[PDB]
Image (tube, rainbow over all chains, first blue to last red; front, top):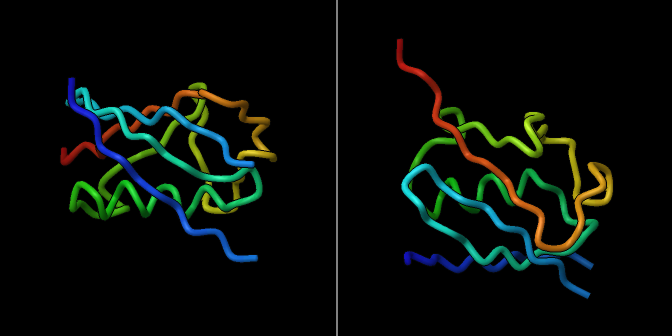
Length: 12
Length: 77
């Protein structure tokens, strides 16, 4: 199992 | 709140995309694009078979939580 984590930045 | 989209690569990589429902999918495409270190013009994002546009959004495409996205590669020739 290969998991890559991506976090997204959201502008208010 | 945040929505979790299931983006999977042809290699079998599953990314835990923590994004919102109003955040542009264009940013999502670029994120994975930069993550793997490839060009955006090299990969194609497909949602339920339909290609994702730079003007598309989760709320627009009616993307629900835990929705899957397929990423294909552009044929060289």
